[PDB]
Amino acid sequence: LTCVTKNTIFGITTENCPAGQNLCFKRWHYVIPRYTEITRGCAATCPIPENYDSIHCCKTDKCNE
Amino acid sequence: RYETVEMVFIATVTGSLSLVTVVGNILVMLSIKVNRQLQTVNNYFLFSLACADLIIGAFSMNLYTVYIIKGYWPLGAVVCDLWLALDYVVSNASVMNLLIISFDRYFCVTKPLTYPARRTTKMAGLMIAAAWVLSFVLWAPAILFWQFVVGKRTVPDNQCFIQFLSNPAVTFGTAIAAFYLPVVIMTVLYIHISLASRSRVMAARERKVTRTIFAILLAFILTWTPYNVMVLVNTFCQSCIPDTVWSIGYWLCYVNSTINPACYALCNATFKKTFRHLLL
Image (cartoon, rainbow over all chains, first blue to last red):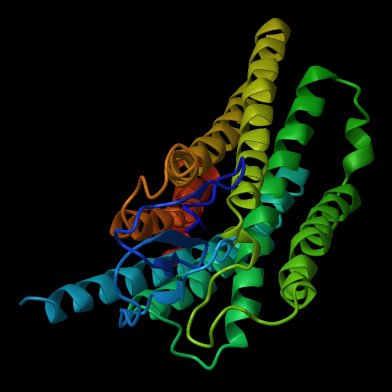
């Protein structure tokens, strides 16, 4: 399925990772009062206990805009 | 030995830096208001910059330390938004203050009759207030209101980041403008001032003032360069830069505020001789 792999000043980049890592985890990790590093990727585990890094699951065609 | 000693080290050094910044700013401005032998607009600009410097130093470093001591915002939010807006607005206000100091110096040097007697003291205070209110109305209401514009405080009750910095485009634009536009303006104005002064050439005091302005500009650019360099690097790839290096970079982003009160006495001879008297 399709998920936005990342965000950039130019625009979004939707991707379709194969049947491996069939899950879209989206993470926010807050490093500075003025910097929050962001990931949106494919993985194979939904629960994902967090080390203060807010994460959520997605398995749709547009979920991490 | 493993982590507690490092935490004590960091907390103590940050507290010492905050205290030395506070005492330096208060002593230099008390000297300004007590000596009363100086009534130039540049000294009023220096006073305003020192006030902004103490605010930045004390409040920003204290709250950034209590944020970095654990990894979240221990306070029950609310104070987070106010402190964040205050820090960002006073940083921008200091940038605009240095901008208008550069404008004033370029105007004075480039024209011997650029209404030099029009300044007096009211114009300096008017310019300082104008820069402060401009920075305020430009940044603070946006900080307080765009979160509600989105609809709700998406920032959790334990985190203390900025809403629009989630968008990389906003980060890139604000960084490039609010750093390099003042930086390039300083560069071109410094070149113009140098050439005008060379063509034109009391001289000792004028050179002292020029060296003081140059030292302030150099300290500001040297301290704030790494932050913007890494911000640009984050526009090259995704997660090009680690996290602890980001922490240290934004930490020495306040080394400008640390340096300025000391550099005042380091470069200005009258400040140097007043420093010894006012330490006692």
